[PDB]
Image: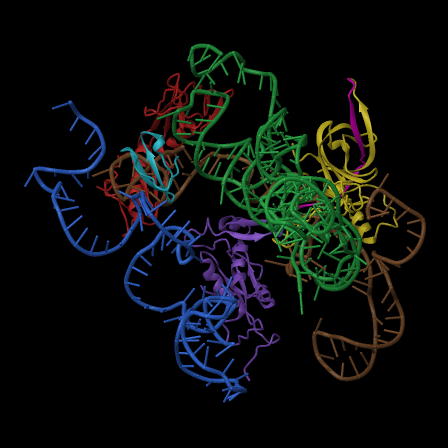
Chain colours: A yellow, B purple, C red, D cyan, E brown, F green, G blue
Amino acid sequence: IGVVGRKCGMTRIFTEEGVSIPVTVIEVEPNRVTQFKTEETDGYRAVQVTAGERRASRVTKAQAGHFAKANVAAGRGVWEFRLGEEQYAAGDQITVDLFQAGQMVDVTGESKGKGFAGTIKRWNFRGQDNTHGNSVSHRVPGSIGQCQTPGRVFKGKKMSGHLGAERVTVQSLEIVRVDAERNLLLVKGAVPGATGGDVIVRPAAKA
Amino acid sequence: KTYTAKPETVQRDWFVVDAAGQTLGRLATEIARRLRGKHKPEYTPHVDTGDYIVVINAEQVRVTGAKTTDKMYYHHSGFPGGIKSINFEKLIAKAPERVIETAVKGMLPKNPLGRDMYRKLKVYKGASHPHTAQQPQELKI
Amino acid sequence: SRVAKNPVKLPAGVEIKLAGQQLSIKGAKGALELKVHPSVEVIQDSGELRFAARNGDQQTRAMAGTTRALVNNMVVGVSQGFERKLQLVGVQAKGQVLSLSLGFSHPVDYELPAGIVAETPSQTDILIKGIDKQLVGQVAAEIRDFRPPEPYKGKGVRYADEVVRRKEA
Amino acid sequence: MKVRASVKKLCRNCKIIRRDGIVRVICSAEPRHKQRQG
RNA sequence: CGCUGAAAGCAUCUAAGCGGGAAACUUGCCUCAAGAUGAGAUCUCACUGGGAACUUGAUUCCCCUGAAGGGCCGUCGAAG
RNA sequence: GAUGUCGGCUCAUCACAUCCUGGGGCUGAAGCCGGUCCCAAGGGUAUGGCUGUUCGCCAUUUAAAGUGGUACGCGAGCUGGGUUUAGAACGUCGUGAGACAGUUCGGUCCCUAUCUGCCGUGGACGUUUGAGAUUUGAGAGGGGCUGCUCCUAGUACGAGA
RNA sequence: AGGGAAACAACCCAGACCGCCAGCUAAGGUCCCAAAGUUGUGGUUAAGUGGUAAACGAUGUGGGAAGGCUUAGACAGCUA
């Protein structure tokens, strides 16, 4: 179980003893249960949620009927949460209330798309020398493989292209503040993605 | 000219093999024999005149000697260093039907016909199969 | 001579259950001893119990002897309380769990399963009581690897005998 | 243990055992005459 | 490192049968993943008209009808 | 009718005959240390002064600075210091042109990738009427390192240290 | 050339005049890839030996010859 919110940028909190703790603030408009997938009817236990406000003209008839079984009147995206043993009816509303402070949590978003990186930026390679006789290749990868054994490049060779919008989980981030009146998690540190990207906050896998 | 079987008017039957203590490859050789259609006088080597074989208790299949803890199964994942192995008993715990499938697959030809014959083998795990509509009858009782 | 042709000579207080393929031994001071007797084995009856093989193998020749030995210590453990006196350093026996601080910062607590029981007759000693010698010897070995005997000064948990190899530097 | 290609009974208390396909030697007196395969 | 234990009245980790045991191995952690042609599963939505020829998984042709939705296009993006 | 060296850079990949880290046995192993031999390949595994160096010798680190295969991996990825064409000089040999178990200064490194491979990213079709979304996970990849001060305790051990 | 030895001038069998939807064989083979014995009788072998290999080391097991210790009561285990 977890929650779906959007990243509102990073801020800071000073404690009274004087340490500034770096804080990202994950705004969680309250998530609305659409299905409850049971192992009898679906093979596994899970719950679908929704987070608010799509236009009427952007919700298709299949999608509107799915959002009208569950009397939810629902919004951008649909997300899923594998469950162990929890019971949610298909109209319920899970909020930031499933988090306390302290409360180590795992946060996943989509990382910021760097476009088509080179091997220095993508895989932290070394550059060759810039001046000592070096011909045209100052920033290129070096050799790829070995000569005639094997006579081909091994799979998974580190080359260049698209440091992009992959899914990244950042795990064991402490919850600084659960602010349920205006629906906020304040989370210690960095979180993957830009401001306003969708971000999934569920408790820590390494506890 | 001699007879050629032709894939529109080939007769196929459904059969249940109960692998409840059978030797692995001595079961697989009769299964592969019946998937190619070697037991029928209408055997033509370029058309599959075989039968559909259901195998039910495919974790009660049995290897002789010390092949239970031994008999590694290998596969290379494609990446360097990526050779991967599993023995008989951890494969019969993980995916029990994969034993009696890779035995029969290795004894079929390495053809698109061998793929088409392998599609007629339906091995399962427990004592039942989801094929009561095709009505298979038991063989090698 | 060979041991399978040596009969069991069970006392009167061992009321067995002949079942055809597996033996089931009941009695007082412990009971419920079941053993799946193997295929190459004969279990017959008289005033006493006795065993014989079935076929001319060297594999069953070991098996009839071990079946007589298993039912020998099985019967004599249904009759008597199999023991062991493990001598150690510091034993605070309290209940179904055992508590011993063998020279570490933590006192490692050892629990005892069904069957076995351990007592505290002295300050440095443990007497065990059980109905099968299998589990008696197994829990004695499970106590023993908590701290094996150091040779030089001599520390750890021992057996009842003294054949521990001691060295001087 | 002491791994050789030729295990022997070094003293009278040594005893040769085929265990799990390995020719080992157990000594009831001195564990330095324990030796593994041969 | 063993318990019990014979073959081999004993002794023996073993031959049957039971245990402990490492960053190795399989999970656990993260990511991709049904082109997994074995192409899986859920929830929801859409379509509920005639006729002719020839050969009746029936196909082809004409008329009407083109839905759910997808796209082209435009304004763009912390996506490229 | 050409398979272009040694070294360095950049990037590697496997083995295990294991350098560290992990698990053990024996000891002429009291403890801190060790010696040797098994088991283990998961991850790690210096920066420099000199010389063209590989190596080596030093300096200073580290838990450790492993050994090897890969065209002594890798120049259609770079260098071009060494060898190394043409210039010149020294010593030596030769009457000489010239030469060298030799030294010495100087001296052009071409290619826009078709195919396999590899890293990315699409277009087609198929999944059995079609569609919007959400998914299970067969399988695959990544990851996996380690030091120090303290806390029982100056205790167990050791005459003591 | 052909067939066999997986693939393999030189090894084995055999020397292709042409056609055949005829038969019998050689080397090699007869569970399935793949044509033919899941053939018969008697054994051996538990290592996957077969399907890589030396000095030497092993109560691994089958067979065949021989000695003496062999109930006045032997080979390891209890009552001076």
Compared to B47, does E2 lie above or below?
Answer: above
Compared to A51, does G65 lie above or below?
Answer: below
Q: Residue F129 in the image: x percent, y percent?
A: 75, 63
Note whether residue C28 is visible.
yes
Which of these two is toward me, F44 or G31? Answer: F44
Query: Which span is picked out in magenta?
Result: A17-41
Q: Residue G2 in the image: x percent, y percent?
A: 50, 76
- Position of the N terminus of chain B, as image quadrant, is bottom right
Q: In the figure, residue C162 lies in which quadrant?
A: top left
Q: In the figure, residue G41 lies in which quadrant?
A: bottom left
Viewed as shown, does residue G13 lie left or right of A18? left
Compared to F142, does A184 lie above or below?
Answer: above
Note whether residue A154 is visible.
no
Q: In the figure, residue C25 lies in which quadrant?
A: top left
Which of these two is toward me, B90 or E76? Answer: E76
Q: Residue A53 in the image: x percent, y percent?
A: 85, 43
